[PDB]
Length: 94
Length: 94
Image (cartoon, rainbow over all chains, first blue to last red; front, side, top):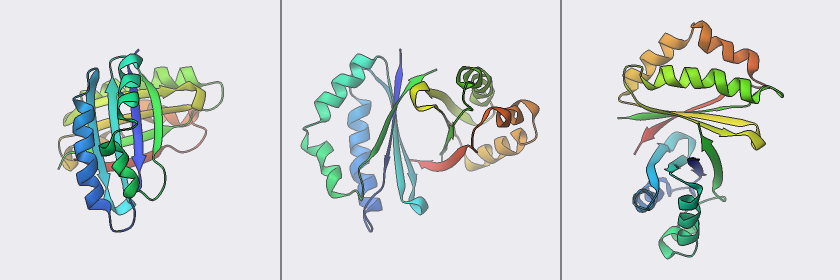
């Protein structure tokens, strides 16, 4: 199986563009992780929503990525920018 | 700008796998529609959720697609398999 993650972020008031800059770098870091087949950043300023989607060659690769990023300062910096916890969902790629 | 659509579907109970077969054919049509840069079907049976994402060269191309599909029988067939209306959202691709 290939898996897909979709993560929806809701930035704090006044921080939409700053968060887009921050998360764009994190998306690049994700794109470069071994086994990531693609990563995309989606913006809807008028809805105060940013969505990241990434595709994984194996569940192995996804899980290695999630473990690797969990304690990293760069990924953890998102907490200073978001109003509520990210909505993180995993899917099977058909 | 490139644009991305994410559409979330909630199939009627007992119709998850039938819905996946029907929507898979629609995703294939979309994938090779003029201006489509990619189309993906995501399944989460345990959440009774299916998600389609597609990427568009231009907003013009997306809008031509939405107009083209609006009255087509195969796209309309989805409505008899849905528990609630689809959640359709458009984004700017960063």
